[PDB]
Amino acid sequence: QKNMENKTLNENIPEMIISLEKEALASTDPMAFVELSDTDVIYFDPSLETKIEGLEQLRTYYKGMQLPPADHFDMIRPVVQVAQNIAVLTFNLDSYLSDKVIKWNCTEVYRRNPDNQWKIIQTHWSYVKPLD
Amino acid sequence: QQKNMENKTLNENIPEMIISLEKEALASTDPMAFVELSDTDVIYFDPSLETKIEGLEQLRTYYKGMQLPPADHFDMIRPVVQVAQNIAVLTFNLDSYLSDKVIKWNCTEVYRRNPDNQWKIIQTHWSYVKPLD
């Protein structure tokens, strides 16, 4: 499974976490990140007055926007900090949609649950220098 | 609490403690408060950076140029702390009152409990609320 450790591609937690994020970003299914998120997920992006709280609220939010994936993206210098059952992934992202780049900051926090799946418990998306 | 005893951890309300640390740093007279509260491997974002800050030395250099605190008054909105073993994820919104102006913020802080039972920031993400509104 893409979000579970194994003896091959998912042996190293940082490489697994980075691959998982890239796979969700490339998915045509707008539910991809929802399916990866846990029931207690907390989510921020630039369009929300305050953070979204809980998986059902996140699901409703993702359903409402119908966001296409980028035509292509570049994940720049992803860092994964691992602490017991938590992996903090941080990166910058150059996302291309219809011939324009949108540059993002991202923090994801993944938790290894008792069934050995890594699930997103926190997401924070922001623009790079939106006002300069 | 016997689990905390075997683990030599404090019998504290972790969410309340983490919220109190954050509020203290925000309102601190020491402009380097957040640098002191951060660990060597800290990663940091804010709306002025073209790419994320990595490492405490980079964070320190950045903070040396900032005048802080930026506001005497601020309101922390619906802080949530998710606790996972030696990690606490603090998320909140913050209304920061700069004299006559207000900046509305999103914030994610990740704190990690070190072996000495000190909670240190390993990740900070500050963003504006609805900057393109």
Image: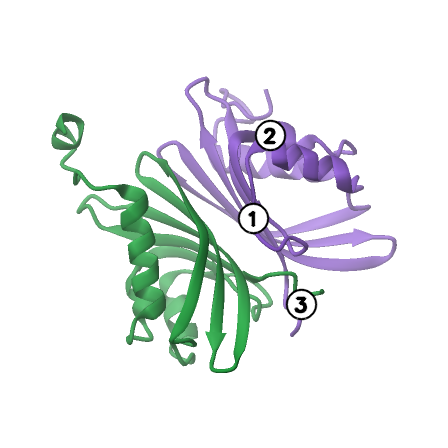
Chain colours: A purple, B green
- Kind of residue indicated by mark 1: Lys
Q: CA distance from mark 2 to mark 1?
A: 18 Å
Q: Position of residue B114 (x, y in %)?
A: 24, 46
Tell me, for residue A51, which label it has, or none: 1
Q: Position of residue A109 (x, y in %)?
A: 49, 41
Give the label, 2 or 1, closer to the camera.
1
- Kind of residue indicated by mark 2: Leu
**Image quadrant for the N terminus of chain A?**
top right
Q: Position of residue A105 (x, y in %)?
A: 60, 56
Q: CA distance from mark 3 to mark 1?
A: 19 Å
Per the image, the residue denoted by label 2 is A36
Per the image, the residue denoted by label 3 is A130
- Kind of residue indicated by mark 3: Pro
Which one is in front, B43 or A6?
A: B43
Q: Position of residue B57 (x, y in %)?
A: 36, 67
- Look at 14% across and 29% down and name the residue there: B1
